[PDB]
Image: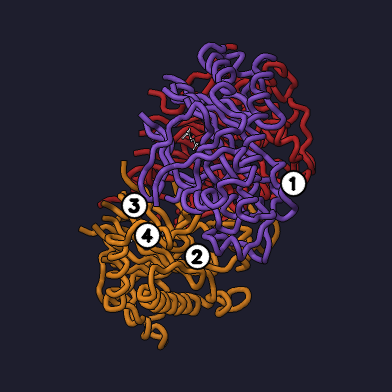
Chain colours: A red, B orange, C purple
Amino acid sequence: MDTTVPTFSLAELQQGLHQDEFRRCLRDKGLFYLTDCGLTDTELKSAKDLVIDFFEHGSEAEKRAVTSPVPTMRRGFTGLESTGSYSDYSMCYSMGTADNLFPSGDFERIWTQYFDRQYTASRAVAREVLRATGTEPDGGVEAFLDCEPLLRFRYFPLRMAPHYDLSMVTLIQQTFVSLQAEVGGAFTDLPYRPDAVLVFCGAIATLVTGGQVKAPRHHVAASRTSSVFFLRPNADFTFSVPLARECGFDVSLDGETATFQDWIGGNYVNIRRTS
Amino acid sequence: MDTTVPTFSLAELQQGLHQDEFRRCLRDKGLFYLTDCGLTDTELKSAKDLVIDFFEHGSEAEKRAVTSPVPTMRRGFTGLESTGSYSDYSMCYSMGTADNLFPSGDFERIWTQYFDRQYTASRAVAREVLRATGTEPDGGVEAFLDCEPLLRFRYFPLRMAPHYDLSMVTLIQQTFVSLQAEVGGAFTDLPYRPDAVLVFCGAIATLVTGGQVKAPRHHVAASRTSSVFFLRPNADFTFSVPLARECGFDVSLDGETATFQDWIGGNYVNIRRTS
Amino acid sequence: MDTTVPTFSLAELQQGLHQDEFRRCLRDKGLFYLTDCGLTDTELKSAKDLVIDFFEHGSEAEKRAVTSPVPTMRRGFTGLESTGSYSDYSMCYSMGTADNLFPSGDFERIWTQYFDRQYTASRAVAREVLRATGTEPDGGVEAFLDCEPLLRFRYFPLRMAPHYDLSMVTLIQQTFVSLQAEVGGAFTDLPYRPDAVLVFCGAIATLVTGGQVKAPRHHVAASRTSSVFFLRPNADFTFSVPLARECGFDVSLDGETATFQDWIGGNYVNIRRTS
Ligand SMILES: O=C(O)CCC(=O)C(=O)O
Ligand SMILES: O=C(O)CCC(=O)C(=O)O
Ligand SMILES: O=C(O)CCC(=O)C(=O)O
Ligand SMILES: [Fe+3]
Ligand SMILES: [Fe+3]
Ligand SMILES: [Fe+3]
């Protein structure tokens, strides 16, 4: 096996090209760069610039106005820990399809457009993962993809321990190479590409497809920023319990079918550590 | 905003005074000192002295007689890890409303009285949090407050990573300032007050009130002792799922209402780390 | 109390001997060595040798063929983290009663026989724990013991933080003493014995017996290998909620009975840290 992290054109995949290469990538590696998906550094620049201005120069009052009363990183501003501040180590801004907290109309306009482009690209590449593996989710493809996404931008003025994601797919845009993944048993660099987004397959891809997609571990070594988009299923997403057991899930589920809520519990869990 | 940690008289709050100051404190800070609540260093001294005597001079046999067969820190004596002993780093004594383990009748009498005073003060200040925010829990106020409290005394012959509490409220009495909380975006000292208890609002205050109360992060830096009282809801405490989502809870709950058990699972979880 | 870790003959226990010594060991210590159970270094040697050959000399392709697409350590090969590899720190091989991944017919034959001997010994010693404590599980003894075991072999070319196990029982065979447990309040060595297996009682022993069995904390200090066999209950294992509370379990369970799934959730959790 070549341990190269491949690149695919979303448009070419949607035209039915490279299907054998794509299927092999999904099973053996579970990560790839994606071009021709409506996301490049051009779309990132406006959003990145205005949130860094907010991190660096917004006042405490402005920040409090867009901070949730519980520090979950679901929506709005968060100072994130590893005299002073938890913001000394890192700062985050989070959003979803609704219940958002924006510091101004300008920010709102720019970040709503950026979110929509990310959400569209993530549903599109998940649709191709499903098609290439012959997978029809219980309840159908479009209701599975109309889901509960989370976007988080993180600024760092290990940075992240080794883990796998529990998403369907995760899309990463970035600004020494900090991001690393296991490929062919060795740590492999994942540098930025101005022309492409990085796609990690998550454990829900593995689950829905019956084990045809790998969910790879990755870590962040030690300024930098990243945009991380999690495509996450609805709580009522339903799957086969025996099939989950056949591809490595250590479930404690009675009965033949279960939901995402049954498996994970009452709160989303975005990442998991093997150790 | 002034980043002063305020002090309120429980008696004055119950008389209907300072309601605007109290409401602003709950939303913007989520912590305060509480006087005139039946708890001062006078009530702490007997309980503190006899448990330290037990930690320092009780024998292994005496300690085993009040150690649970599973090391959960729910009831009785625990040596708590960060040749030797896990007790080398810290020692704990835990109790609740029933199923307690006491090393003697003297200890039992002193600690039952101390627990009752803490439980009374915690229900009283939670009642004022609910009243000041116009909150009627599903099932009513008194059945919500007749709940599942946990008292833990900890001796240290970071000491605790940054976290928020998942209680309704937490009451802390203490014996260089080790306890720190985020206030106005900066780490703020929380020293002892012989005349007052420190109150942290927890995530259940945020949840029941629909987001009108902040649950602040805090940490313990590096001998010292502390008494920590968690006022925790019953497993059947029921809330609105859409309202929880509107104030930052990243729930994975199908349907319009849920219970505390639905959210947290089958075991109490007292603290949560953002990271 | 003597803080000696005792040794029992499985055959002698099954003949009804040493019942008072055995009961006292279970309540006060919750660990012991077990002889005369069909497990010695003779049965370990073939299995150990062929998996170390695989770790050291199998190629990446061979390893990928027996790696699950999600890195859960449930089945097959795993590189386990604390340029390079996560395999640099440790390597694991896992199996159960079905859905196994074997690198060859030789390996399969040797490891299926080894698993069967471990599973038999673990059910046998759990049967004696139940008998000695007068315990009839809901649904009966044999359906409780026909369960969901997990075998993991780990090679290390703290190694493990202090924890207790959430199994019924755990059986350990091993190849400076790395493994340590709390006994009588002090860290006590658990060296290998060519003629015996080490048995840890887990929290499910405590639960099913109503608090008559201790689940002791233990840790691994810092090459070495170990074989660790977890005897884990079925998801539908049912117990009394008030009795669980009386022996230290901090449950958040409405109602009078619950299942293992109700308590732990939708995924097995094998170990728990007090801290
Ligand atoms: O910051 C990055 O590039 C990666 C973060 C990541 O893997 C995550 O948040 O799951
Ligand atoms: O020991 C203290 O003062 C604080 C402990 C604390 O925050 C907790 O146990 O939640
Ligand atoms: O490796 C050992 O000897 C112990 C491992 C252990 O306690 C566990 O995996 O629970
Ligand atoms: Fe990730
Ligand atoms: Fe706390
Ligand atoms: Fe263990």
Dot 3 alpha-carbon crowd within 10 angstroms: few under 14, some 14 to 19, many 20 or more: some
Residue picked out by circle 2: B206
Point out residue B228 in the picture as x, y percentages from the top left corner. Answer: 38, 65
Per the rendering, the mark at residue B92 is 4
Query: Residue A12's quadrant in the figure?
Result: top right
Badge 2 sits on which subunit?
B
Q: CA distance from mark 3 to mark 2?
A: 35 Å
C216 or C245: nearer the eye? C216
Are the residues tagged 1 and 3 within 8 Å (C-beta)? no
- Give the CA distance from mark 4 to mark 1: 39 Å
User: Would you say the beta carbon of the disc 1 residue lies within 8 angstroms of ligand 3?
Assistant: no
State the residue position of label 1.
C143
Q: Is residue A177 above or below residue B80?
A: above
What subunit carries mark 4? B
Residue B93: % across, % down: 39, 63
Count every numbered label the image shows and give the total: 4
Disc 2 residue lies near ligand 5 with CB under 8 A: no
For the residues marked 3 and 4, what is the alpha-carbon distance in whole angstroms?
Answer: 9 Å
Amino acid carrying label 2: it is Thr
Q: Residues within 10 Å of mark 2 (few under 14, many from 20)?
A: many
> Cα distance, mark 2 to mark 1?
44 Å
Residue closer to the observer: C91 or C129: C129
Residue beneath the point at 40% across and 74% down: B108
Q: Amino acid at mark 3?
A: Ser
